[PDB]
Amino acid sequence: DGSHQYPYSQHPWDAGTMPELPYKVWLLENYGYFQFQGDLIDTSVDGGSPDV
Amino acid sequence: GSGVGVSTGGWEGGTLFGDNRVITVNTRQWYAPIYNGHRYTKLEGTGNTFWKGIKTPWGYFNFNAYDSHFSPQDWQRLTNEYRRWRPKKMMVKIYNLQIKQVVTLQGDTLYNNDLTAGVHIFCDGSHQYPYSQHPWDAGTMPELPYKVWLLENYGYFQFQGDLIDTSVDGGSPDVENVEKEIAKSAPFYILENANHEVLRTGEETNFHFNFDCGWVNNDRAYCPLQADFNPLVKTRRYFATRNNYNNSGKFVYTRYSPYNKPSQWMPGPSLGYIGNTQSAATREQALGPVTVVTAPPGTSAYTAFTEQQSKTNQQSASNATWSGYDVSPVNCARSGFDKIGLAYDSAPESELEEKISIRDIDNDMSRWGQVFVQDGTNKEISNDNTGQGGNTRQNMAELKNVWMFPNQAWDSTPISRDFPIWVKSPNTDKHTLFDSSDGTLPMSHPPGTIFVKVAKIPIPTQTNTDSYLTLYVTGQVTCTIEWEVERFMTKNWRPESKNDVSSFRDAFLYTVGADGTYNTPERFLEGMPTRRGINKTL
């Protein structure tokens, strides 16, 4: 993704970078991304009727 | 060259009859006042009607009638000499503009000419603004070239009063309330969004338009659709007859008479509903053969209940007249009901006498009086073999309501001199066959409506409230339409019926009286209808 059209969830200071030892095998990291904030969806979100 | 003191044009008029083309030039003297005080205001019908819309500070040229374009003789010579006609291209020219100011210096009112006052003129060719012009409106171009023509105030439908009614309170948004949504999604149009010209006394403008439309047929069929055949030859077809009136029976076949032959040509569509005549005193309720209540699924129109079969809101037939809009005439190809649907007056703004004219005379035999359907034997079949007949049965019945069906052929209504020329075809996705029971020619894009308002000149006020200068515009408009015509040709030996005046009941007609009152026809024949004598081999 060169345009960064998908969430860039990579953080500095993550343990999944390229190994420093060239002879160690490198297991790629599972990708995932933030979506919503648990306590900002919390109150009165019941789907009984739309609340605009 | 140009300026305040040279005229932009001159009076053009007359007509040119030709083999392939007729060109009718007409000029009128018009004036537009200040409409509604230079403001858009919500238009609500008094009485019981749910029609609601906008009243606009604008006025418009309505060129749609025949009698405005043709004189009585130009019409007569048109209908007598030509088989069919349609418009090709129209050209309107608005010129010799004059803007006058109305000032009251004393008890008297004096009219003095204010130069440097503009007039807004806007032709909507794309129909981006609501086309609210209706055929059968009293605001068309005058038939008398010497009468001055007051343009009509423009306004348009916005929302339906009983479809905004229920629970529309603005306390909180209701997104599931559908009537709340109709009011939200109803449009509001302003003609100041559009590019348009502002003219002064020295300036002029003109507009061209190219019609794409069907024809207007002036010839009649002398023969019923089903009556055209040769009795001298015997037909090859037989008709079935049940014999013994029981289960053991079978059809026995015998040849048609040479004088009675079956046909493949059905009667054109019709609806046998004559409209409501109950002596109802309310003019704004729907009195018409077919009244149509438009309500979206979730809406409740006027007083509505839920049909428990479908669980949908429906209305009683009495309440529907409140909520609905009639369509007339629906008779279409039935000429028996010609007298029902159309009744109209020629005389505009005349409180003297009604002079209501109704279309009585149609001699065209391609339009049918009645249709009868006969479904079998006159006596119910006995369930046993042998036995004699059974309970009596209704063999024949009148078909009142004839819908569209394959192999239908008919002719449109004969039109009088004073009818509308065209009608706006809706911008809907789907359309069926175009046949108008008022004879109009529906067009996708008819001539664009020309709007006129008078430029607003403010008056400074201490209170800062809106105060405008009182002034109006008068001018001259020349409408020139080019008509595509077809001269008839026939091998008929006998003379045709030509719309002579000798058949008129009133001797003094189409002429002014002692006080200047122009005498107009109160009857449909005196309006010189089409489809009179010219015979059309079926």
Image (tube, coloured by chain):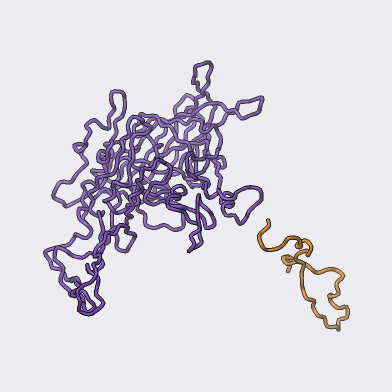
Chain colours: A orange, B purple
How many marks the image carries: the answer is 0
Query: Residue B492: horizontal and vertical position, in percent?
Result: 16, 51
Query: Residue B499: horizontal and vertical position, in percent?
Result: 22, 41
The quadrant in which residue B272 appears is: bottom left
Residue located farthest toward the top when viewing the structure as drawn: B106
Can you see residue B24?
Answer: no
Can you see residue B509?
Answer: yes
Query: Residue B324: horizontal and vertical position, in percent?
Result: 45, 49
Along the line of sight, the residue nearer the viewer: B339 or B89? B339
Along the line of sight, the residue nearer the viewer: B205 or B130? B130
Along the line of sight, the residue nearer the viewer: B376 or B115? B376
Residue B185 in the figure: left or right of residue B500: right
Residue drawn at x 37%, y 39% as measured from the top left: B480
Residue drawn at x 32%, y 58% as measured from the top left: B401
The quadrant in which residue B501 appears is: top left
Q: Is residue B296 above or below residue B453?
A: below
Query: Residue B53: horizontal and vertical position, in percent?
Result: 52, 43
Q: Which quarter shows the C terminus of chain B?
A: bottom left
Residue drawn at x 29%, y 48% as measured from the top left: B338
